Length: 456
Ligand code: HEM
Ligand SMILES: NCCc1ccc(O)c(O)c1
Image (cartoon, rainbow, N blue to C red; front, side, top):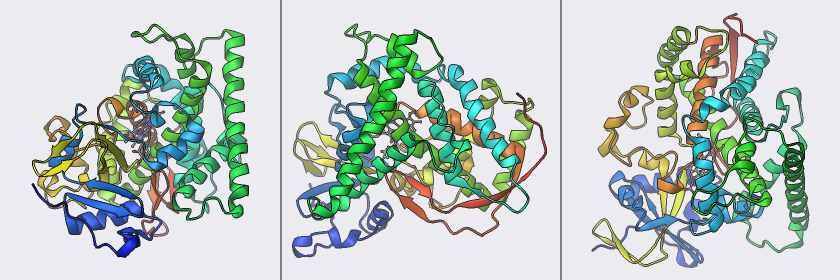
C-alpha cells in the first residue's frame, strides 16, 4: 500500500495550471513520462487517476470491478446524442437493449452487407482526387471527414449528404459539427451562465432540432414506405432484443443514428489521416504498402475478400492507432471498494482514466523504440500481450463500430495506395488538434495519379 504519485499542486488551483493548453492529452502524456504508470490529477472540485501501464490497465479492464464512467465531455455530448450507445450508462435499459440488437449488425460478417455502399463513397473520393488539376493539393482530414460522414450516412440510414458535391456541408453536418464543438467548449467555460453564451445556447438548441428533425423524418419516411435496405436503420426497425423480445423505439433509433455519425465519423477520419501521414513520412513503408495494394487489388473495384487480404495495410492502420489512437482516453469507475495493483486502494465510485496513447508507449511491452513507426510490430496480433493494445476500448463497452471502422479504413487506404503516388510537398509538421478526437490539423499532400482505371 502506497501513496499515489501526483503532479505539483498550486494552492487552490491544484494541478490545473499544468493543463493550460488546448492539447490536454499530449500534456498528460508528458506528465505520465515524469510520474509513471499512475498519477492522481486534481482540479478545483474534480479528481481522477490516469493509468498508462499495461500492468494496471489489465486490472481496470476487469468488468466485475470497473464499469464505463460518463466523463463530463460525454455528459455534454449526451445533450444531443441522448441514450445512444456511446453516451449511456451500462445499467440503462436502452443500453443493453440496443447493444443486443446491434451487435450482429456490426460483426465482421455484417461488413459483407455494407461493403458496396462503402465502395460507393470511396470511388467518389478517388474520383475527386483523379480530377484535381496539376497545381492543386489535398486537404487530408477534410476529405477523410467527407468520406466517413457520407459512408456512415449511406450505411447507417441510406441518406446521401453528398459532401463531395459541396463547399458548405449539408445543414445536418454543419449542425452536428457545431454541436460537437459546443459540447467540447463547455468544458473550459469558467462562467457558463454569463449572457455572452446566450447565443451559444440558442444555437445549440437550433442544432439539436436540425439533427432530430432530419433523422426523425427519415425514420418516419422509411416506416411509411415499408422499404427494406442494406442499412443499420432496416436492422433497427426489424430487430428485437433476444433477451426482452422488445424492439428499439423511434426516439432511441434516432439517437443511435446521430451517435453513429457523431461518435464514429471523426475517429475514423483521424485514423485514415494519421495513417497517410505516417506513410508519407516513411517512404519505405509507403512503398511496401503500395506494393501490397497493387498485388491484391487486381479488379476495377475492390471485393470484400480482397480487402481482407490487405494484411500490411491492416498493420499500417494498427501502428497508426498505436501511436495516435484517435479516441484517446476512456473513463471507468470502481463498482466497489477495491485495491488496484496491490498498492492503491479505491473507494466505490472513484474514477480512473485510461490514457490510451501512453498505454501504447509502455516500453515493457513494445520495446524501447516506442516513438518509431513500424507496422511490423503487428505481424502476429495473437502474440501481443492481452490488454496492451486498446484503441477500441474495453469489454462490453468496447467500440461497436470497430469492424466497420477498420473495414472502411482498409478499403480506402488500399484504394489510395493503388491509385496515386503521394508527395509531402510542404514538409508538414505534425500538429495534433484535440477535440473529442485526435487529428493531424492542416495535413495536406499532393497526389499524382497512377492512371489506373476504376470500375462502375
Ligand atoms: C478508428 C475509428 C474508431 C475508434 C478509434 C473508436 C473508438 C472507440 C472507443 C475507444 C470506444 C469506447 C468509449 C468509452 O469507453 O467511453 C468506442 C465506443 C463506441 N464507438 Fe467507436 N471508434 C471508432 C469508430 C466508430 C465507428 C465507425 C462507429 C459507428 C459507425 C463507432 C461507434 C461507437 C459506439 C456506438 C460506441 C459505444 C459502444 C457501447 O458502449 O455500447 N465507433 N469507440
Ligand atoms: N466511437 C467513439 C470514438 C471515441 C471518441 C473519443 C474518445 O475519447 C473515445 O474514447 C472514443
